[PDB]
Amino acid sequence: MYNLHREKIFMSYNQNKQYLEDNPEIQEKIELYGLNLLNEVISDNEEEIRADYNEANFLHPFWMNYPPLDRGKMPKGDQIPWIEVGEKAVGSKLTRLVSQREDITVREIGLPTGPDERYLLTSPTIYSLTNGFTDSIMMFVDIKSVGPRDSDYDLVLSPNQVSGNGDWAQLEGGIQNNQQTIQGPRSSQIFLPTIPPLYILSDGTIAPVVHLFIKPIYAMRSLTKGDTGQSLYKIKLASVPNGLGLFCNPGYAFDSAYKFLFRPGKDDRTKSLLQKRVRVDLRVLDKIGPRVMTIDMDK
Amino acid sequence: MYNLHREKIFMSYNQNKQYLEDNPEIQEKIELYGLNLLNEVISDNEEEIRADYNEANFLHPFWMNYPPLDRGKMPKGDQIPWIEVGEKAVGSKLTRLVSQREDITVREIGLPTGPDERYLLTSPTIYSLTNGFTDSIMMFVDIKSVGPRDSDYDLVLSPNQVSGNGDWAQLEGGIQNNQQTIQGPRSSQIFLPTIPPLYILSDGTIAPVVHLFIKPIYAMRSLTKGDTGQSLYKIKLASVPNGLGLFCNPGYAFDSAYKFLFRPGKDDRTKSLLQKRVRVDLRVLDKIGPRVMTIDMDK
DNA sequence: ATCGCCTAATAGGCGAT
DNA sequence: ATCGCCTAATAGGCGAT
Ligand SMILES: [Ca+2]
Ligand SMILES: [Ca+2]
Ligand SMILES: [Ca+2]
Ligand SMILES: [Ca+2]
Ligand SMILES: [Ca+2]
Ligand SMILES: [Ca+2]
Ligand SMILES: [Ca+2]
Ligand SMILES: [Ca+2]
């Protein structure tokens, strides 16, 4: 199966990736389109999102005796691992609501690695936006929840959540991304993205990758004497440029105007030097364009 | 938030769980309804499921240099960890298709633990089926993929994927399941389900839990000289009774007619004695009713 | 057939500096 | 503020018996 459509994918990928790389504005258009599409959907279904999210706390009796156990160094002991509440009540719910949009068609293309949510989003809006280049994009959305004890202004991303330059030299070969040296104010690390900047499906469909991050932020009610629960406080939305934009054109990752866009992640010295996660600073990403947004969900 | 609707949930849960327990046929009806609903949907969208699944192999060049690394004891070295392909192309796709059914409404109720897919499925069909008892159920669906080198006739389930008796003695307390001693032909282990047999939402909604397992089975093409890829071969569907049916009425877990329905799982002697996974033998589960089905997807 | 040996990959709370 | 210390929970391939 590996070789059946390989030549056609190879030829199309290389011709199309060059075009994308030389015309960064097209990718930026569809990336902002994806971002604003999530913002719209969260806005149009705010009560539902908050209700199904916060419902986890009301269902407390059903899981109180079997909560996810604490993990990490020195847990304070008053928080409940809230990872899956944001993943389902926010992340999965959004995937369904996006597909219910009148003009949008969703296709779950099989891939062995990647973010929480992945799907080919096809729509006539993308066709005009890209002036006929394509009518589809590969949505790569990952939910990153935090409480009042972690930073609400960063993103810690795994290699499988970032795309690179994706050179594909020879046919019998494949896409390869260059290692990147992340230099922060005090430390540095290597970061190697594993995702290609775009995909070409076996039927010739051109699917530039659009990386979106949804960051639900909960409040710890217990921080207030005798109150209980971890309620939906806000949701940050962030668009991270695909690999061509980050490392090729306009090369945001190397622009002095945006120093420390990337910084060392949370992986410890026991992790493989090539699988370490990287941080993206939302305060800097906020300067390269209308890439970040905050929605108040505490109402 | 923990106490705001607690009394109402408590009162309703206990009255409703007693009714469910004493009328096992209602739960069996909705459980078989959920099973047959997935069978219908897989059947009505077979080309799409197989196409988006198998597409992962055609996209080989895009991930060949960054495949999920091998894990476990003595990997042969010719297989690619295929976990996420089945999760998305089959599991996530089904959740969307079920919600697109005319008469079905889906709600992603937040929960901190549980299976791959979870959602409140509401429909008038459930209302007549349960003769007015309720119009909703909590779908608990987990995707379990296997290749030609693991058994296509079992399921290895985590505590968070099985419900128990769910006694809830006192209000300020919560649901609790009894530990179960799993006795297999050569070994034995404890198994402690963490999920309640039903949920009551803060608005009084009665949501009996319906546990469904989707088992995509891929073929290893490479097992045939020079061919490549891991293609969709079959999909097994299995309905596992909720906790009331397993351990209370009719108590399938303790019925001599179904010896070894459950058996020790895959967790090693280094795992907490209370978090060990348990196996469910599909060949036995197949005897307690029309709980198991096989769909040929290799066409 | 039984069953458990064995490890990749994801996640974010929280302290140390 | 920076950044990495630290561990729960999920998963199924495959050998050992
Ligand atoms: Ca605690
Ligand atoms: Ca639509
Ligand atoms: Ca994830
Ligand atoms: Ca995530
Ligand atoms: Ca290999
Ligand atoms: Ca519907
Ligand atoms: Ca899972
Ligand atoms: Ca699963």
Image (cartoon, coloured by chain):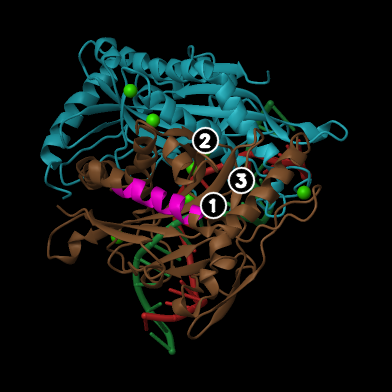
Chain colours: A cyan, B brown, C red, D green
- In the rendered image, the quadrant that contains the C terminus of chain A is top right
User: Real-space Cα distance between discs 2 and 1?
Assistant: 35 Å
Q: Observer-nearest residue: A8 or A56? A: A56
Q: Quadrant of residue A136?
A: top left
Front disc: 2 or 3? 3
Q: Which residue is mark 2?
A: B108
Q: Which residue is mark 3?
A: B199
Mark 2: amino acid: Glu
Q: Which residue is mark 1?
A: A271
Can the viewer see residue A41 in this picture?
A: yes
Packing grade of label 1 (10 A; few <14, some 14-19, many >=20) is: few
Packing grade of label 2 (10 A; few <14, some 14-19, many >=20) is: many
Residue at 59% x, 38% y is: B110
Q: Residue furthest right?
A: A225
Q: Along the horizontal axis of the image, is A219 left or right of A294? A: right
Q: Observer-nearest residue: B21 or B48? A: B21
User: Real-space Cα distance between discs 2 and 3?
Assistant: 14 Å
Find residue A219 and report its horizontal and vertical position in percent. Answer: 72, 29
Please tell me whether residue A109 is drawn above or below residue A212 in the rendered image.
below
Q: Along the horizontal axis of the image, is A211 left or right of A201? A: right
Chain hosting mark 3: B
Disc 2 is placed on an element classified as loop
Judge whether residue B31 is colored magenta.
yes
The answer as to whether callout 3 falls within 8 Å of ligand 7 is no
Residue at 55% x, 34% y is: A89
Disc 3 is placed on an element classified as strand
Which residues are drawn in magenta?
B26-39
The answer as to whether callout 2 falls within 8 Å of ligand 6 is no
User: Real-space Cα distance between discs 1 and 3?
Assistant: 40 Å
The answer to whether mark 1 and mark 3 are in CB contact below 8 A is: no
Instruction: Indicate which disc, 2 or 3, sits on the residue closer to the N terminus.
Output: 2
